[PDB]
Amino acid sequence: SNAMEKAKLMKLGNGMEIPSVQELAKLTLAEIPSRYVCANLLPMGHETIPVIDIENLLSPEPIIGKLELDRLHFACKEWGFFQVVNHGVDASLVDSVKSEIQGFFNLSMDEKTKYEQEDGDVEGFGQGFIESEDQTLDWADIFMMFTLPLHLRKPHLFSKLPVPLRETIESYSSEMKKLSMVLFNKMEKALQVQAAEIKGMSEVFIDGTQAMRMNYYPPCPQPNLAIGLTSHSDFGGLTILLQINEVEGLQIKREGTWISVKPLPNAFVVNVGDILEIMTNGIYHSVDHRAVVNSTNERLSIATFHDPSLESVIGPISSLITPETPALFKSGSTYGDLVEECKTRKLDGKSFLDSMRI
Ligand code: NI
């Protein structure tokens, strides 16, 4: 890289665009710029996340189906995270998702940023804008966009994607949505929610929103000072993650320790979000997780998020409120209002979930 590129990447004021870490990584710096150093710790945990087989889950043989339903129910209660295998998503499609996204991140910055973002429109390539000097930046580049419903797709964003990536993403969206609905429907059965009689789970997600985050984590020279994706719990319904290459990075919090997730070949990693925990009246758990970086290999992933529609009324499903499981969370806000409230929230204090507790 040339000296002007270096200055553009490193001499950053508040209000400037967060720079590309894939570009920063080419500078091969001895120490990472100060903004990537995490300022404010749990130990590492061979206990691994459960595996759920979708063929078993959908088996026409009731004993097979019931066993897998017990496994799903267990994983959602006790782990909040599970791998899915025999998931029905064609191997060729998965290969194309991997190759086209690898292809995409290997394009020039000019080619990755052809979409003209509207003021306040944060979709496409980019982590956003620098907020303050004490803001910590993730060691990661991102491409984020809404994928369902169709009218939430930014048409000019979609038109500026390479054609094979766009077509593959469109197919992947459909398969991810189908898979999410298989899982929502089975979670509803595991919870004994009679969707015909009462306001259940699946009806909230069937016409809900879907979004994708494509993530590129370059190698980092000081991987014990930086983070790929800061510790968080997912806000919405069900997340389905594909790890694109064989580089480990995803870690989940279990009993005050960090546990590595090594995705299986031909597996997706699925987790419960905060809104899903609420809807289940705390029976299913949304778990803290993070992505770490390393000094030798880039890591890639794509996460597909399945959330309520913006006007879905959120609360614990009524048949899950019982004398043995009393109502833990408030009811009655729309999903869109919860999203907006969480953006402000309270500077100091508690998690979104704890803020919603009765
Ligand atoms: Ni997450």
Image: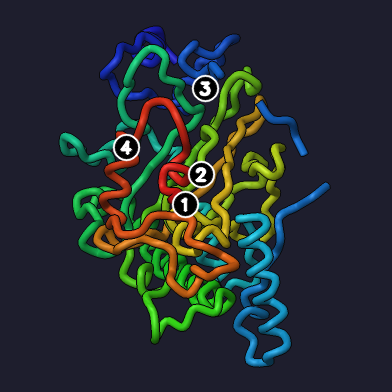
Q: What element carries label 1?
A: helix
The tag earlier along the polypeptide, 4 or 3, is: 3
Q: Which of marks 2 and 3 is in front?
A: 2
Contact between labelled residues 3 and 4, with CB atoms less than 8 Å apart: no
- Choose between 61 and 106: the one closer to the eye: 61
- Where residue 298 appears, as percent x and y from the top left, is 59, 34
The residue shown at (23%, 57%) is: 152
Q: Which residue lies furthest to the bottom in this view?
A: 61
Q: What element carries label 2?
A: loop
For disc 3, the marked residue is 25
- Choose between 70 and 109: the one closer to the eye: 70
Contact between labelled residues 2 and 1, with CB atoms less than 8 Å apart: yes
Q: Is mark 3 on a helix, strand or loop?
A: helix
How crowded pointer 2 is (Cα within 10 Å; few <14, some 14-19, many 20+) is rated as many
Q: Residue 233 carries which label?
A: 2
For disc 1, the marked residue is 274
For disc 4, the marked residue is 343
